[PDB]
Each structure stands twice: as C-alpha cells, then as structure tokens.
Amino acid sequence: YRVVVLSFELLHAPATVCGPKKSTNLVKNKCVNFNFNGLTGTGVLTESN
Amino acid sequence: NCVADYSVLYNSASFSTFKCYGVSPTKLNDLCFTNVYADSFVIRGDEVR
Amino acid sequence: VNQNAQALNTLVKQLSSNFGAISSVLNDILSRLDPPEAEVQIDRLITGRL
Image (cartoon, rainbow over all chains, first blue to last red; front, side, top):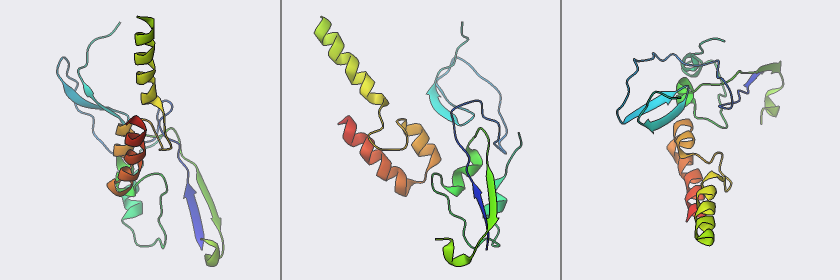
C-alpha cells in the first residue's frame, strides 16, 4: 500500500500556499465582513497611521 | 508558492483512505497555510491502522 | 478604584485561554472544522467562559 501524509501548519506567519479564490475589490467606511488570507472577521476598515 | 486544488484529490476514487485529523476536507479549499510537507512511503496494508 | 479596575482587567484576559480546545478564537474553529466537532469544541469554550 502506498501512503502519503500531508502535514501543513496553519496561520502563524505570512501564508504562501492557498486558494482558487478570486479577490474582490476593496471598500471602506462600512460595516462589512472581511477575509484576509483566511483571517475572517467583521467590522469597518479605515486608513491607518 | 503555488495554488493547490485539493478537491480533485478528494473527488477521485483511487484512494482507499483519505482521512484528515485537524480539518474537514470540504473546507481545505478556503484556507491559507505557510508551507506543506509531503511524506511518502509504502508499507503493508495491515499496518495503516 | 484600583480593585475594581484590576478585577475587570482579568475578566478580559480570560478571553484568550484554550480550556482544552484547539484555539481560543471561535472564528477559526468555525471556518476550519465541520459542525459535528465544532460543537464538541465550542462546548469547552463556553463552559470556561461561564
């Protein structure tokens, strides 16, 4: 029997390997539910300092 | 540094055992990882347990 | 004043503990697993927080 093991490690650094998912455009100043490289959340985005 | 599509791995019947332990395979198409390790070998069937 | 503040402080801190689950953030558990085990983990989390 041929055996292969995949042992990815997940979400602690700049991610590199993922996603047949198309990125949409960026909006601002609205309560929106967002996703950044698997970091999922909800809130309003703003320009930072 | 690539774009992996795990669905084709799931949607093929060639594999007798396809078992994940910290994720659900239906979700693997929406996550981002740092890097992955593929460990390959061949053994006797009675030991896969 | 001191005492009150201090107490409140630690409350917030207890939001960053595992209590035995895989992660301390509900969003990861929900977006990573399927429900029949997400239940088993969310159970531990809510027990600790209560």
